[PDB]
Image 1 (cartoon, rainbow, N blue to C red):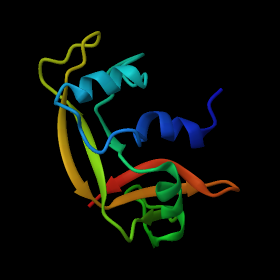
Image 2 (tube, rainbow, N blue to C red):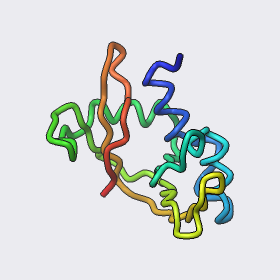
Image 3 (cartoon, rainbow, N blue to C red):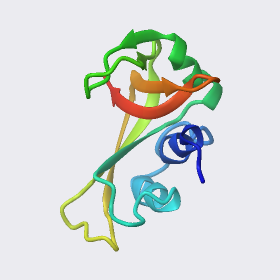
Image 4 (spheres, rainbow, N blue to C red):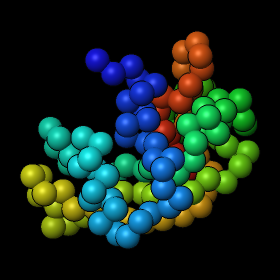
Length: 124
């Protein structure tokens, strides 16, 4: 049973890549990190940083999470991300995603001792 902290890592964390590798990168990852399982996930962004530099966002500028809450942090720093937005042509079983690559600020929600990222909230 995945602890949230690792679930986050499975849906959000690809450190082994500098950035998107192609464009069916999205399709490879969605699939490969089980997001396309019980349905196709609407959208999912992936961070291309070390877990260590990401977990340390929990000590960076504290912001309100989109949903109204208060355990969210935004990186002081810019970080490379790939947004997997799903498309029109996407019919789970076959979820089709569009690789949109960027190098921007992540805002995540932190929880637990150790206080790690748990939810990816947004990116600006």
